[PDB]
Image (cartoon, rainbow, N blue to C red):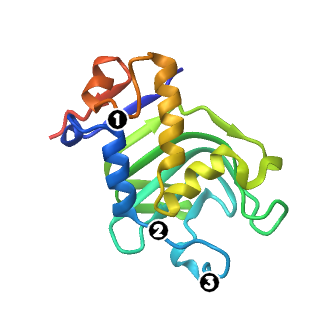
Amino acid sequence: MSISISYSTTYSGWTVADYLADWSAYFGDVNHRPGQVVDGSNTGGFNPGPFDGSQYALKSTASDAAFIAGGDLHYTLFSNPSHTLWGKLDSIALGDTLTGGASSGGYALDSQEVSFSNLGLDSPIAQGRDGTVHKVVYGLMSGDSSALQGQIDALLKAVDPSLSINSTFDQLAAAGVAHATPAA
């Protein structure tokens, strides 16, 4: 099935490009980089983990922002090719206030803003950090939603060539691809 999007009515008249640009700058950069992952503050986590799962989730350093990546995900840690997220990425959910974890049976957001699902991305381990899955999620970690934007743009075009990353959420809804929250 094709990409499916959830958005809060707040963003009805926003474009996906405007939204993701604003969100990524709001989430910022957790500085997850060589020599800068020295404790648990910026690792994120996997469910069930320790380095694989159906979710990877990460909270912003200085805001309440967070995302959950959903799929069939794997992380190489120190093993060649080192620090590669690979596997299947089905969903990215963006919002505020991450809760839970492996110990409680899953991650959740208290307040989801927007989600993209049925992304259908699938990168093999041997592609290392050049894998699309890696670049999409690592981009979110480091305050750059470019890779995610590109993949959403492609998926949208494949549905209907009038759709793009620059469409409004309401347009995507009209085109059958997105759905506004009934709330509040």
Of badges 2 and 1, the one in the foreground is: 2
- Tell me the distance, in whole angstroms, between the alpha carbons under discs 1 and 3: 35 Å
Q: Amino acid at mark 2?
A: Asp
Determine contact: label 1, label 3, CB under 8 Å: no
Q: How many marks?
A: 3
Outermost residue toward the left in this view: 184
Q: Secondary structure at mark 1?
A: strand
Q: Nearer the viewer, residue 51 or 13?
A: 13
The residue that mark 1 highlights is 6
Please give left or right for residue 125 compared with residue 19 in the image.
Answer: right
Q: Which mark is residue 38?
A: 3
Q: Nearer the viewer, residue 110 or 22?
A: 22
Above or below for 72 versus 28: above
Above or below for 31 versus 131: below
Screen quadrant of the N terminus: top right
Determine contact: label 2, label 1, CB under 8 Å: no
Q: Which mark is residue 30?
A: none
Q: Secondary structure at mark 3?
A: loop
The residue that mark 2 highlights is 29
- Tell me the distance, in whole angstroms, between the alpha carbons under discs 2 and 1: 24 Å
